[PDB]
Image (cartoon, rainbow over all chains, first blue to last red; front, side):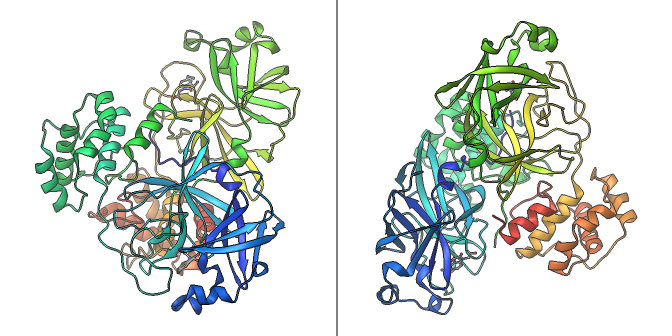
Amino acid sequence: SGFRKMAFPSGKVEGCMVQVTCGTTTLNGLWLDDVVYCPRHVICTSEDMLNPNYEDLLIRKSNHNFLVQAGNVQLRVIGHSMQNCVLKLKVDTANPKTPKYKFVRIQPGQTFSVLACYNGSPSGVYQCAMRPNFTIKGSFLNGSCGSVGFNIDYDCVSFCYMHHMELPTGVHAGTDLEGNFYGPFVDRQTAQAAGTDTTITVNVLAWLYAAVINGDRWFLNRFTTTLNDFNLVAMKYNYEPLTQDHVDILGPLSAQTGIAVLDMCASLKELLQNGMNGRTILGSALLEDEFTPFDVVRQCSGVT
Amino acid sequence: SGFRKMAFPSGKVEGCMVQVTCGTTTLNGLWLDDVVYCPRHVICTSEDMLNPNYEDLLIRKSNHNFLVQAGNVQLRVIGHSMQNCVLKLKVDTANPKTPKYKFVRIQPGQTFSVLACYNGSPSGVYQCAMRPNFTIKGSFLNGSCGSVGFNIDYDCVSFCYMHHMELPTGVHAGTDLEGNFYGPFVDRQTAQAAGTDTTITVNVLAWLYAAVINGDRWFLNRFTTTLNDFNLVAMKYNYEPLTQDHVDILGPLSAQTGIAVLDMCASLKELLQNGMNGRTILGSALLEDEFTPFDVVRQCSGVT
Ligand SMILES: *[C@]1(O)C(=O)N(CC(=O)O)c2ccc(CC)cc21
Ligand SMILES: *[C@]1(O)C(=O)N(CC(=O)O)c2ccc(CC)cc21
């Protein structure tokens, strides 16, 4: 019993974190096999950040200008290339602690763990979600760029995010491990605003199922709804539209609890219209949307 | 910018988790040097749990009745002893991945990370706090016993908790690594009720300082208070009494923000009396009390 915001064990990713320094800029790198992946803005000064031409700035850099340190030992850089917004630094040593891994580009609403690092050293791990506007709400200070987001399936780490930026509003932006930003963001110190940060409806429903499984049932109402009626209310409350794909994904949670997906939708609709009335659900006074249906199944079943 | 519920990187603790089986019961163990620590109720059947006499049950057990597996390899048990509510299993091999470590008994209000495990395998990591009634609100399923709580200071892991029990209300109880339970709980399947779960006042204030540092300032009021006036309101709201020791501990956060501790107390007093009014602080609709002042300093400064 009990339901917590839980991150994946971070050991497999801690064994991959390195420090990358180019001139006077230092950030984090991800060492997998004989390649170190890092934000391409490691080559920039704070002045260059205002309007960088990365291809031009990279002409002035050779292999020996990238200092990669793993623990307290220096790695030899034998090649470098820019792929989208990441630099790939070929090193002469394969990372002995390289886990089984994949690079995945996640969809909005998907959750992942972030191992926040500074100078190639892990400081903490937390769980977050790719917002529908393609930002994440992380906890990142100067030097955190290059910190990665990931999911784990038994022994394989699927890297899905690398941190690159903080928008002027304090929210965060980054890329997949191929260097492609999530959303319309660019690695430039220019005013970039995020779109509407809607609530991830399918995740709120999954978390309502977790609440029922853990005994918080006060919010269960005597109503049902349809996808179209529910979505009219969801639109009004800045909730993402619910599709039949989302209903399908909640099927195992509906089966475990005996609560039809549309009945849970009607309970959510009443919570939106009436509010919490000073009550809590799983120790929260707001509806939590950073647990996917897969997260709820995993946590409630004890997947290791 | 941004403030998250963050756990310590778990790698150092993942390298210590083992599976301990005695007869038909399997739980987790913590392998440090040549000793494996685990809940003494690994020797019990579900029937024994109702009214166990551990000393008597242990007479029927020899070294070879404790099966310890680290990864997919069996460890040889060459000694066993009961210390309070934990068993210490001496093994013939020192754990090669033993980090620098200490065993600490924490005070209520102190936070720590839990690496939830099943069959000696890590499933997730989350941050929690020792409640003032000496329970924790974790996420633990059957077989999670033996999972540990810890804090890290650079390279030294201070183990503070081992999971032993779930109370009939869904809250959790356990011991320090010397086997002494936090609070009045016993390792027996008998109705045990928790006392008042008060709010950790000093932690709420630390989190209000984190909110100010991250730009959420709407709640800052034009008032001040005294410790005695504040405590009269805190008692009414089931908040822990604030002492001058707590004020001292908030000193660095008071200095960083320029907000006197007693002014923050008056802002908290107004939040308690007026409520949030549908507003949020750091994405929360309730006042968060599972960040200590040390956690706020660490996260806001980037300690690795
Ligand atoms: C990136 O290098 C970094 O560490 N940060 C700080 C952060 O808080 O995220 C940051 C902020 C902005 C930019 C512009 C692309 C880069 C970085
Ligand atoms: C302990 O062996 C365990 O794993 N659990 C399950 C839990 O959800 O915490 C448990 C519950 C009760 C007791 C009685 C002491 C032991 C354990």
